[PDB]
Length: 339
Ligand SMILES: CN(C)c1cc(-c2ccncc2)c(-c2ccccc2)nn1
Ligand SMILES: Fc1ccc(-c2n[nH]cc2-c2ccncc2)cc1
Ligand SMILES: [Zn+2]
Image 1 (cartoon, rainbow, N blue to C red):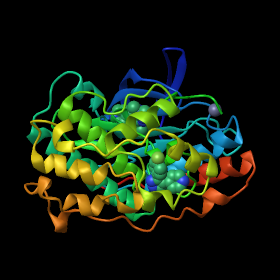
Image 2 (cartoon, rainbow, N blue to C red):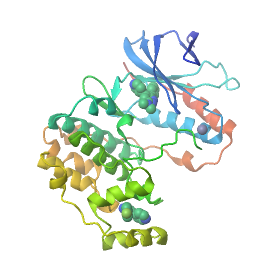
Image 3 (cartoon, rainbow, N blue to C red):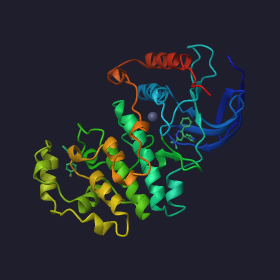
Image 4 (cartoon, helix red, strand yellow):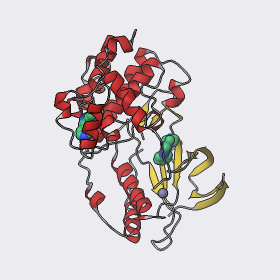
């Protein structure tokens, strides 16, 4: 066991091992507080996230276990991975706080899209890295469900990695329409829709669907992609949604070459395959990587898939003490990756 030292940053106390020095607050939120630090053992700049109230509720305890299980499993250049995980507690009885450590990423895609207008070559590299990480995530039968610019970390090298009422976001401009319709059988291609919205934002500099609420969000989406056709209509079970979409004003599918003027016709062709209403016909991450848009980056031998990921815990109804004990087991059993 290492030696821990204590200090108070902002209004939160931090008890981290001695190997992490020069702790500096970089961000905060519902998830928890993140501090930049220097790791003296490896010489790397790392990010240390202290989870907030990790076991205040069953929702918190299970989400703490889920995040730790996910981060321990992701080993991919374009997905955030665990360099270390620790707790200052010496036993299960005192187990109260959880700290996670990864490589320090300086900014996100929002701090880049607003500060500059990305060239087409930068859009290719950034979207390729997202899809390369999405193929890995999706190969483990994992759906991100919340892909957005603020969840995409980027450093100076333009290297990219994918990252109750608390943390409520009113409208998600990047959410697939099938989720906005509260469809329960949405698939992995909900993430591909978000990539299309992100890629459109990088090409134009504007939010593609900046809706004000869930109803306004659907109206903005339907104005571009058109109202559902007959094949899609046959798949809507909720009469409330089927009658709503039929009662609405019939909008035709717009010409994407007219919407995204001056853009690379290869990029427009990809956007047409990503921003498809019917999720059955949406391009997948693996298919998108082979698109001619990424001809200079695509390498079929260098786009790996993930090891099988056991999600059986997601259907379990355990107690807070059980999720807590399961999380403690994952903390101790953690082995770091080779330097
Ligand atoms: C919600 N959000 C923006 C983030 C950012 C980061 C982050 C990652 C890398 N560098 C800087 C910040 C983290 C994080 C996750 C695990 C360990 C440490 C930090 N979690 N959430
Ligand atoms: F307006 C829309 C927006 C999205 C969809 C949709 N695309 N893929 C699946 C669905 C869907 C939505 C609701 N219920 C079943 C299926 C259908 C109509
Ligand atoms: Zn909560």
